[PDB]
């Protein structure tokens, strides 16, 4: 019943609550994805979960239903609500039209939801930002990146984590046509892109791939090592 | 922050709204002293008309809750009739809900309790009037009560209410340790010894209840005039 | 601070004159009503070149014969574009005909200055919609475009510029339009976008243009049509 | 409370004597002395006004007892019996405070 | 109408500013002792009014919750009366659904549950009454205390109100685990006798016991009786 | 003037860990700096006495 | 200025401190003038063109079935208030099946715009209506105000520098209660032609007028139909 | 800043949002009401701004229940609001209890309405003093006057407005009890012309034995008879 | 009024949440009760309030709360709030049974409680639940597992994490992740509590099983006097 208008226009057209959510996604993990023309691929430099984590419940990588899956970046507990409501309405859109639900529609639902929390009476618009990847009825490995202002863009790298302005300018530099193959050059581009930022993948990185509406497979740190070694060898 | 703005706890306790509401009942000040008789709870108060243009019958404090309970209040008179109407409401609601006519004590508990929820929640001021209210039940003698604007009803013999409360209760304390159905040397003489007017029978309102006749009666200048000329001992 | 429903010591609301800002922020869109159509264009300001530019929706078709062109705080319009199309098919549903442009523009602009803190159920709005847009549409009266404000003020327009280029492009558009389409208003409007140029020489990747002509319904231009026009300049 | 924090330091003072604003087991002795240098007619009571122990100096004991005698000068009396004691005390027997019900 | 925003909030130190003020308003309240004893408790308290003017049979501080559970307070006046109203209502919900007098522990669960949301929930300030509970509940007696935060602890003896450090230290000195009947009343009387501000009048104290036959207030002829046996 | 400081020497009533640690950091950085400029230590300074 | 959280507060003299400032917010609006004869009342409005060119934000409005209005202040709030006035005027067409009288119309909107002046956090309806209609007796004309205090006036002018139009129109009341339509609306346009910045013309573009009275519907004269009203040289 | 909210007292117990509403009727014109044995006569000062306003541009003598009246002082929006809910209140009494509303109950009802409306920070107080008045066949000429504080007193000759400091003196020196209302309608103009110290286009209404429990603007003849109390 | 609200649901200009990290400093004032899992079951190890004799008997303590047959929880921070929420989450556990006839695998429960506690820090204007409580449990799906949550909302599998003051870094140099042998987990628990001690001022509680059903023991008195003499040096 709390009805104070929080998200209000200040002077010079500046909607301060949303830009405060922009630092709130600037102060998270470092998520990254690549649309690799037959495959899509993610990655989020994780912390010290080997000391005493459980790797099963440190997941920045979730799954929406089977094909679309997202990597949030920021506040890591307001995100899980958006995960749950994405899964719920995604099952409702399996109820009505009965498709392998298109990635455009669910990312319009996420952006419309966060824009509906930039409007309602006193509820602090989210501090998350997504990487809605996936497929559709005919291949088309579309990636989407939302925003706490509820603006989604259909771009192809969108490194939107904490130290990821360097990663998106790197990915601006080093993604033209060399990653059109099956998986190896794409995943090599991702693990190269996050090994720009931190250290070795035996403690830090974890990834996920998705191939043609089957087999959302994560990569355990034994397998990530091979790719990391190849990158190191260069 | 907002200790003296909202009904919340300041440091060292002492929420700064109820004593700001206590100082509200001294505004102007038309002052009641209630006298209790082992068989008759008399009521006294002073009432001043400003300019002989008011209707003196309409201005009063002296309200009637039911056929057995009267009341008099000395707070700010805006907040008075909002409080006495709810007391009439809970009296008639008691008689409709629980059979017998309400006895005088838990009426004052109940209006003390809604005054509590005024001074518990925010966004409402604790309304500044205290309810000297008398009445007789079948079991005990005549009673008298006063809920404050904080909700602390006590069960009194003889307090007072309004401006000059301390001089009145000092006079009554000095004049009750000696031992009074007539109440001729107690009821008016608290006023005439506190503020020294030695009233003509206009400005004083008196409301009695007796064990022989429990109906609440507001007296007129004839019988209060005999009551005043009985101060010739 | 102060709230949203307060008037400013200049004379207008706070949130409305603050909602006139964040229209200077955001991309620029222009529209020209002609005698045989209405053309809309927007330079949707792609940030990086690593990416896909043909999914920044700034020309949105309300119906087959109403297309809008928003700017400013993007994606805040989607609720009132949703209300525009739901109201459109409600009109066609209940009345079995087309619409005007002042009925969709009448219906959307009622939602602009409709907000507040303490009101009905919390599905209401807090801030005003900080998105200025204009409905290019063809009617049985004529082709026309209705420039809205965030204040709910909507006006008849035949040559209107929004966004950051609301002064220089509007003053340039003030002197170059009087007559009719004859295919060259769409080529003398991207010329105004050619003077506006921020990052790139206005190729068929960073501007979206769409016309609404009375013969057809609308035409969101694809790439080879755009670069067919850009080759002619 | 603001004396100086260099006026002591074991050399300039080395001591500190608190004066208590006395209570029950002392107040009785103050009344016994100050009444012991007056004329009393034993209608007075001692421990009744030792009771209500509320915030007195010795100076205001001399004020209520001195004031008791001077209030007995009204009827040109060489003693004091009942009211001048109680009377002066109540008048200036701390001219009250300001309680504050509910809390307490 | 209403506020629907909490006025109790977290300090920049990381603590509740209103609750420590509530414990200040409790600590400025009238002193009250409570002694858990081997068969039954005693919950004494101190009723000092302004003058000798009031009806000391009118208001109570020992008052039961409907079966065998009395509760005595220290602090704010009428907020206590609200907690008695809510406590009697919760005990009667429990009695109408489970057909036994309520276990004391569950009554302290529900009274501490209702005192919590006044540390939240829309403009209400917390109560500032740390009342303490008694109760015989089957086999061995219980004793508790619901702070205006909402916490509660069970023990063998406590005090509250004014100068309660002296009450806790003094009861820590004089307590025995078998100390059971009227000796507890004795030490309760000489815990209130410690300060009292003077003369130990029977009309200014009232006690309540839970002697395996329901909580009951003590008549004023019984407290003065043991005040004759001091 | 502030004659507060009263001459004291070694009559400290049963503190030996404390005087070992304060003499570890109050006369070694004064009367033997040579093992601090060869031990790699920069400088110890500032002691907080909480009790 | 602690009287900025402020339709609940009182300035210490007498002032409510912003619903007179809404009266400022209709002083800022565009100028207009209405008046009444013994037979039929007229409304005249000049329409500001703050653009390329336009319909100049059409002021006088059709509410009714002879109870016409003339707004001057906020436009969206004006349209909200005339959807109210419009809807319950049609409701009085529905239930009672008579023309709703003009006085009860303006009184109950005078009780409808009075509620947000009372309560909390709700701005007053910042629009100065200049309503005019022909009930059973003579054709009334009511200024109402954002302070919810209407006036049973004759020949009132409100808007930007409309005080000069009043002081023309105050000293020319003697030739009212006569002066038929052809010479009445000339007498209102030469009352409007003082609020203009002293440069010469009430053009056919910006002047839109409305006529209501005996044996004629409230009739709007737009860009074309105002051209038969032409005279005056000053 | 103990101001600006009706739910916050002063440090000496004085709710400033009420006394700021009280001066907010002291900057508005007078409206006197004089009781006599056959009914209550009202008279309101008017402060006609321009010639543009016609006769009765703003009613300030409303009526409520076909017999009680509404001489108001302060903000006409707020006074008109409580006028129409007084109409609804006597509507609920006559519909509910059948018997025509006695005025004491209506003044206590509207009084506790406008008082209970000054206990919350979510509302402002009203800014309008006003007075009532009527008589039933066995009531007596009851009139009451109600402040923005919500207090309602029975009067004889109460006067609210700007110049009530002047107006209370002549009503006090006028013979109050025993004259038959027609003269005092005439005499009301003497009070209004004295207290107006500067178009004063006044307006009168009453209830009386010439009315049998009703209200009329005067009928219209004393407006050219009590106008002849110029030069006094 | 908007002058009075604490405005809990506001992002900082640094992007964080003021009322949330004030709860994180509330944990460091009062809080103990580490938890260790093994190949066998999981234990809490806890501290009571002080040395204050005056405490007759706790059935369970004020620290370890039973939730199902196979779960339990321990509590840091403000003890008044968490009591409420643990009864709240207890309701959740039982209604999962009512919906599914399963003993509620504990990650469902932790997810539900973290969603409602996130909902109190999301909107409503209230203060957040100042408790970083943690959970132990078992399901047929996974092994013995403990989760740990905080007033922000996120949680995790936190194999040996303690809460409260004097922060767990020694445990991430001592815990053997493969095998632990729960008696030696008791030994490590009294090691850590011996650095940060009979059952007057300790409260240790284990979760084990026999033949399939789980057994939650609160480790009655004399077992603590066993383990406290199981040292010499440590």
Image (cartoon, helix red, strand yellow):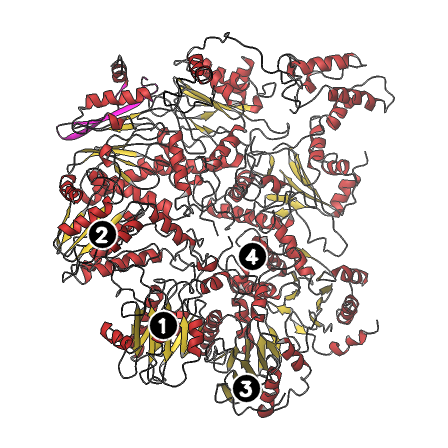
Residue to which mark 4 is pinned: G6
Q: Which chain carries label 2?
A: A
Residue to which mark 3 is pinned: G213
Whether labels 1 and 2 belong to a single chain: the reply is: no
The residue mark sitting in front, 3 or 1, is 1
Question: How many numbered marks are there?
Answer: 4
Q: Where is residue E29 in the image (x, y as percent from the top left)?
A: 54, 29
The residue mark sitting in front, 1 or 2, is 1
Q: Mark 1 lies on which chain?
A: C
Q: How far apart are marks 4 and 3 (CA)?
A: 42 Å
Crowding around mark 4 (Cα neighbors within 10 Å: few <14, some 14 to 19, many 20+) is: many
- Does the stretch in magenta take in I204? yes
Q: Judge whether G6 appears above or below C97 on screen.
A: above
Residue to which mark 2 is pinned: A33
Q: Judge whether G38 appears above or below G10 on screen.
A: below
Q: What element carries label 4?
A: loop
The residue mark sitting in front, 1 or 4, is 1
Q: Which residue is drawn at 73% across and 72% down?
A: H200
Q: Judge whether B222 appears above or below G107 on screen.
A: above
C-beta proximity under 8 Å, tags 1 and 4: no
Quarter of the image where the C terminus of chain H is located: bottom right
Q: How far apart are marks 1 and 2 (CA)?
A: 34 Å
């Amino acid at each position: 019943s709390y009805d104070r208008a929080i998200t209000v226009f200040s002077p010079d057209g500046h909607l301060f609550q949303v830009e405060y959510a922009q630092e709130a996604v600037k102060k998270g993990s470092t998520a990254v994805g690549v649309r690799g023309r037959d495959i899509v691929v993610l990655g989020v430099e994780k912390a010290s979960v080997a000391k005493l984590q459980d790797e099963r419940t440190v997941r920045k990588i979730c799954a929406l239903d089977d094909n679309v899956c997202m990597a949030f970046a920021g506040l890591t507990a307001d995100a899980r609500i958006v995960i749950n409501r994405a899964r719920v309405e995604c099952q409702s859109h399996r109820l009505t039209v009965e498709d392998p639900v298109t990635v455009e529609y669910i990312t319009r639902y996420i952006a419309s939801l966060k824009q509906r929390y930039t409007q309602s009476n006193g509820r602090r618009p989210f501090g998350i930002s997504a990487l809605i990847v996936g497929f559709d009825f005919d291949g088309t490995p579309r990636l989407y990146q939302t925003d706490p202002s509820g603006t989604y863009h259909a771009w192809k790298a969108n490194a939107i984590g904490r130290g990821a302005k360097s990663v998106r300018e790197f990915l601006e530099k080093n993604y033209t046509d060399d990653a059109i193959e099956t998986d190896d050059l794409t995943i090599k581009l991702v693990i190269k892109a996050l090994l720009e930022v931190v250290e070795s993948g035996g403690k830090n990185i974890e990834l996920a791939v998705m191939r043609r509406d089957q087999s959302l497979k994560i990569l355990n740190p034994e397998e990530i090592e091979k790719y990391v070694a190849e990158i190191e060898k260069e | 922050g907002f200790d003296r703005h909202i009904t919340i706890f300041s440091p060292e306790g002492r929420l700064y709204q109820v004593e700001y509401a206590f100082k509200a009942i001294n505004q102007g000040g038309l002052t009641s002293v209630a006298v209790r008789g082992k068989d008759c709870a008399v009521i006294v108060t002073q009432k001043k008309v400003p300019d002989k243009l008011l209707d003196s019958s309409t201005v009063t404090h002296l309200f009637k809750i039911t056929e057995n309970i009267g009341c008099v209040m000395t707070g700010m008179t805006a907040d008075s009739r909002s409080q006495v109407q709810r007391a009439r409401y809970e009296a008639a609601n008691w008689k409709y809900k629980y059979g017998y006519e309400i006895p005088v004590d838990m009426l004052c508990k109940r209006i003390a309790d809604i005054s509590q929820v005024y001074t518990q929640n925010a966004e409402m001021r604790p309304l500044g009037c205290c309810m000297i209210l008398i009445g007789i039940d079948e079991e005990q003698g005549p009673q008298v009560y006063k809920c404050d604007p904080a909700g602390y009803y006590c069960g009194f013999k003889a307090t007072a209410a309004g401006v000059k409360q301390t001089e009145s209760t000092s006079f009554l304390e000095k004049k009750v340790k000696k031992k009074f159905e007539q109440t001729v040397e107690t009821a008016i003489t608290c006023l005439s010894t506190v503020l020294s007017i030695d009233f003509k029978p206009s400005e004083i309102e008196v409301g009695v209840v007796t064990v022989e006749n429990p109906k609440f009666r507001i007296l007129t200048e004839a019988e209060i005039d005999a009551h005043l000329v009985a101060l010739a001992e | 601070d102060r709230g949203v429903n307060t008037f400013s010591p200049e004379g207008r609301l706070f949130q409305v004159e603050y909602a006139i800002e964040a229209i200077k922020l955001g991309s620029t869109a222009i529209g020209i009503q002609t005698s045989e159509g209405v053309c809309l264009a927007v330079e949707k300001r792609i940030t990086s070149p690593l990416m896909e530019p043909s999914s920044i929706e700034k020309i949105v078709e309300i119906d087959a014969h109403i297309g809008c062109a928003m700017s400013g705080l993007i994606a805040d319009a989607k609720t009132l574009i949703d209300k525009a199309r739901v109201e459109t098919q409600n009109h066609w549903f209940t009345y079995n005909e087309t619409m005007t442009v002042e009925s969709v523009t009448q219906a959307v602009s009622n939602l602009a200055l409709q907000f507040g803190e303490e009101d009905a159920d919390p599905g209401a709005m807090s801030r005003p919609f900080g998105v200025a847009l204009l409905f290019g549409g063809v009617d049985e009266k004529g082709p026309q475009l209705f420039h809205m404000d965030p204040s709910g003020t909507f006006v008849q327009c035949d040559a209107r510029a929004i966004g950051s280029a609301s002064e220089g492009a509007q003053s340039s558009l003030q002197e170059v339009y009087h007559k009719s389409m004859t295919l060259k208003e769409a080529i003398k409007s991207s010329l105004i976008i050619l003077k506006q140029v921020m990052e790139e020489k206005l190729n068929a990747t960073n501007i979206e243009l769409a016309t609404v002509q009375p013969g057809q319904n609308f035409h969101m231009f694809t790439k080879e049509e755009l670069e067919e026009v850009i080759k002619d300049i | 409370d603001t004396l100086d924090p260099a006026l002591l330091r074991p050399g300039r003072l080395d001591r500190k004597i608190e004066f208590p604003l006395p209570d029950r087991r002392q107040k009785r002795l103050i009344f016994s002395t100050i009444t012991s240098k007056m004329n009393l007619s034993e209608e007075v009571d001692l421990e009744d006004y030792v009771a209500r122990p509320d915030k007195i100096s010795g100076a205001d004991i001399n004020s209520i007892c001195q004031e008791s005698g001077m209030l007995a000068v009204r009827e040109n009396r060489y003693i004091v019996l009942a009211k001048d004691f109680e009377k002066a005390y109540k008048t200036v027997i701390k001219k009250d405070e300001q309680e504050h019900e509910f809390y307490k | 109408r209403g506020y629907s925003f909490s006025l109790t909030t977290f300090s920049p130190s990381g603590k509740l500013v209103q609750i420590e003020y509530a414990l200040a308003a409790v600590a400025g309240g009238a002193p009250s002792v409570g002694i858990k004893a081997a068969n039954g408790v005693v919950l004494a308290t101190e009723k000092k009014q302004k003058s000798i003017l009031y009806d000391e049979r009118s208001v109570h501080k020992v008052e039961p919750i409907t079966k065998h559970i009395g509760l005595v307070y220290s602090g704010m006046g009428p907020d206590y009366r609200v907690l008695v109203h809510r406590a009697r209502k919760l005990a009667q919900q429990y009695y109408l659904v489970y057909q036994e007098p309520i276990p004391t522990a569950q009554l302290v669960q529900r009274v501490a549950s209702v005192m919590q949301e006044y540390t939240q929930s829309g403009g209400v300030r917390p109560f500032g009454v740390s009342l303490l509970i008694c109760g015989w509940n089957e086999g061995r007696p219980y004793l508790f205390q619901s702070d205006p935060s909402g916490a509660y602890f069970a023990w063998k003896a406590t005090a509250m109100g004014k100068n309660y450090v002296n009450g806790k230290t003094f009861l820590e000195k004089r307590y025995n685990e078998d100390l059971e009947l009227e000796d507890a009343i004795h030490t309760a009387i000489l815990t209130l006798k410690e300060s009292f501000e003077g003369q130990m009048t029977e009309d200014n104290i009232e006690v309540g016991i839970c002697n395996e036959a329901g909580f009951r207030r003590l008549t004023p002829t019984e407290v003065k009786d043991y005040l004759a046996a001091i | 003037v502030e004659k507060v400081p009263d001459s004291t020497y070694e009559m400290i009533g049963g503190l030996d860990k404390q005087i070992k640690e304060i003499k570890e950091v109050i006369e070694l950085p004064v009367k033997h700096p040579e093992l601090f400029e060869a031990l790699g230590i920069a400088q110890p300074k500032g002691v907080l006495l909480y009790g | 200025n602690q009287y900025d959280n402020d339709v609940t507060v009182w300035s210490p003299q007498g002032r409510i401190h912003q619903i007179e400032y809404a009266m400022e917010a209709v002083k800022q609006g565009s100028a207009t003038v209405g008046l009444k004869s013994k037979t039929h009342a007229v409304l005249v409005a000049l329409k500001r063109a703050q653009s390329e060119l336009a319909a100049h934000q059409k002021k006088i409005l059709h509410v009714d079935n002879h109870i016409g209005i003339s707004i001057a202040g906020l436009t969206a709030d004006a349209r909200l208030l005339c959807n109210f006035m419009r809807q319950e005027c049609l409701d009085s067409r529905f239930v009672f099946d008579r023309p709703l009288p003009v006085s009860r119309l303006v009184s109950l909107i005078g009780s409808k715009t009075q509620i947000p002046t009372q309560r909390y956090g709700r701005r007053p309806y910042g629009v100065g209506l200049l309503i005019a209609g022909y009930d059973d007796m003579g054709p009334h004309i009511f200024q109402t105000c954002p302070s919810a205090n209407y006036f049973d006036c004759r020949a009132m002018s409100i808007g930007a520098r409309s005080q000069s139009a009043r002081t023309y129109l105050e000293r020319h009341m003697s030739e009212f209660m006569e002066c038929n339509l052809d010479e009445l609306v000339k007498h209102g346009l030469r009352a409007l032609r003082e609020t203009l910045p002293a440069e010469q013309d009430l053009t056919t573009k910006n002047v839109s007028i409305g006529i209501v009275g005996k044996d004629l519907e409230f009739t709007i004269y737009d860009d074309d139909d105002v051209s038969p009203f032409l005279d005056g040289l000053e | 800043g103990y101001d600006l909210s009706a739910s916050t007292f002063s440090p000496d117990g004085r709710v400033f949002q009420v006394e700021y509403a009280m001066k907010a009727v002291e900057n508005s014109s007078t409206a006197i009401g004089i009781r006599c044995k056959d009914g209550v006569v009202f008279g309101v000062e008017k402060l006609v701004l321009s010639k543009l306003y016609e006769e009765g541009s703003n009613k300030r003598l409303f009526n409520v229940d076909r017999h009680v009246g509404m001489a108001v002082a302060g903000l006409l929006a707020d006074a008109r609001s409580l006028a129409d809910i007084a109409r609804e209140e006597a509507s609920n009494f006559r519909s509910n209890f059948g018997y025509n509303i006695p005025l004491k109950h209506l003044a206590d009802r509207v009084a506790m309405y406008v008082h209970a409306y000054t206990l919350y920070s979510a509302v402002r107080p009203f800014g309008c003093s006003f007075m009532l008045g009527s008589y039933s066949v066995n009531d007596g000429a009851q009139l009451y006057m109600i402040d923005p504080s919500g207090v309602s007193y029975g009067y004889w000759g109460c006067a609210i407005g700007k110049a009530r400091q002047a107006a209370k003196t002549e009503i006090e020196k006028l013979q109050m009890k025993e004259m038959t209302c027609r003269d005092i309608v005439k005499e009301v103009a003497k009070i209004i012309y004295i207290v107006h110290d500067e178009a004063f286009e006044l307006e009168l209404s009453w209830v009386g034995e010439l009315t049998n429990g009703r209200h009329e603007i005067v009928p219209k003849d004393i407006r050219e008879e009590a106008e002849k109390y110029a030069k006094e | 009024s908007r002058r009075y609200d604490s405005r809990t649901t506001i992002f900082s200009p640094e992007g964080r949440l003021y009322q949330v990290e004030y709860a994180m400093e509330a944990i460091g004032h009062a809080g103990t009760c580490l938890g260790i899992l093994a190949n066998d079951g999981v234990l809490l190890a806890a501290e009571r309030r002080n040395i204050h004799k005056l405490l007759d008997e706790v059935f369970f303590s004020e620290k370890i709360y039973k939730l199902n047959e196979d779960m339990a929880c321990s509590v840091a921070g403000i003890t008044s709030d968490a009591n409420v929420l643990t009864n709240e989450l207890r309701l959740i556990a039982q209604r999962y049974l009512l919906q599914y006839q399963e003993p509620i695998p504990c990650e469902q429960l932790v997810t539900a409680l973290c969603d409602i506690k996130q909902a109190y820090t999301q909107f409503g204007g209230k203060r957040p639940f100042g408790v970083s409580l943690l959970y132990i449990g078992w399901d047929k799906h996974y092994g013995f597992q403990l989760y740990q949550s905080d007033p922000s909302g996120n949680y995790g599998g936190w194999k040996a994490t303690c809460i409260g003051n004097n922060s767990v870094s020694m445990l991430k140099q001592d815990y053997k992740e493969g095998e632990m042998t729960l008696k030696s987990a008791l030994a490590l628990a009294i090691k850590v509590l011996n650095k940060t001690l009979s059952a007057e001022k300790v409260e240790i509680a284990t979760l084990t099983r026999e033949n399939g059903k789980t057994v939650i023991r609160v480790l009655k008195q004399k077992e603590v006097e066993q383990l406290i003499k199981k040292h010499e040096e440590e």
